[PDB]
Structures are given as structure tokens and as C-alpha cells.
Amino acid sequence: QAKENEKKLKSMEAEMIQLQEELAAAERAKRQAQQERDELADEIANSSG
Amino acid sequence: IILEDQNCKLAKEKKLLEDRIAEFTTNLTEEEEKSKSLAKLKNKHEAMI
């Protein structure tokens, strides 16, 4: 049962690992958007402004 | 790509401004050349008038 129970741990790790895949990309998306939401914004006031 | 996209569009501004500043500066001096050229030619009419 220990080996069988361990299989559920590695299987459940896929959920945490899968969530980290989307969480890492989703969290990184904020950095990319923030770098562009502020850089272009400051430049928009200089170019468009 | 997001960072390069901003730099790509922002690089055109620095290149356009650097290229436009050369034309804008020459455009302002163009009026002086025409004004000075016309003023010199107009001086002949003044002396004749």
C-alpha cells in the first residue's frame, strides 16, 4: 500500500506541477504586461502626448 | 517578443525623431534661405523703387 499510496502522491503532483505550469505562465504574463503597460504608457505620453 | 515589440515600435520613434529632427531643422532654415534670398532680391527692387 505504501508503494500504491506513493503512486497517488506522484499522480497528485501532476496537478500541482500542471497548476505551476499555468501559474508560472500566468504570473509571468503580469510582468510582461506590466513592463509594456508602463513603458509604452510613459512613451505614449511622449509620442502621442 | 513583448519586450522586442515595444523596443521595435519605440526604436522607430527614436529613428523617426532623429530623422524628422533633421528635416524639421532644415525646413525651418529653408524659410530663412528663401526669405534671405527673396530679401536680397527684394533689396534690388527697393533700390530701384
Image: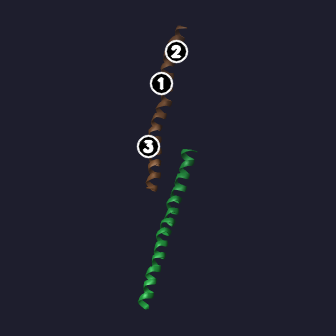
Chain colours: A green, B brown
Query: Which label's residue is closer to the chain start, 1 or 3?
Result: 3
Observer-nearest of A27 and B12: A27
Q: Do labels 1 and 2 share a chain?
A: yes
Query: What residue is rendered at 48% in x and 27% in y?
Result: B30
- CA–CA distance in space, label 1 to label 3: 27 Å
Observer-nearest of B9 and A46: B9
Q: Is residue B7 above or below residue A32?
A: above
Tag in front: 1 or 3: 3
The residue at which mark 1 appears reads as: B33
Query: What residue is rendered at 45% in x and 45% in y?
Result: B12
Looking at the rendered structure, the secondary structure element under dot 2 is: helix
What chain does badge 1 belong to? B
What amino acid is labelled 1 in the image?
Glu
Q: Which numbered disc covers residue A15?
A: none
What amino acid is labelled 2 in the image?
Lys
Residue A45 location in percent, x, y? 57, 48
Badge 3 density bin: few <14, some 14–19, many ≥20, Cα 10 Å: few
What chain does badge 3 belong to? B
**Image position of A5 (left or right of A38):** left
Residue A21 location in percent, x, y? 46, 69
What chain does badge 2 belong to? B
Badge 2 density bin: few <14, some 14–19, many ≥20, Cα 10 Å: few
Query: Which label's residue is closer to the chain start, 2 or 3?
Result: 3
Q: Which numbered disc covers residue B42?
A: 2
| Numbered marks: total | 3
Tag in front: 2 or 3: 3
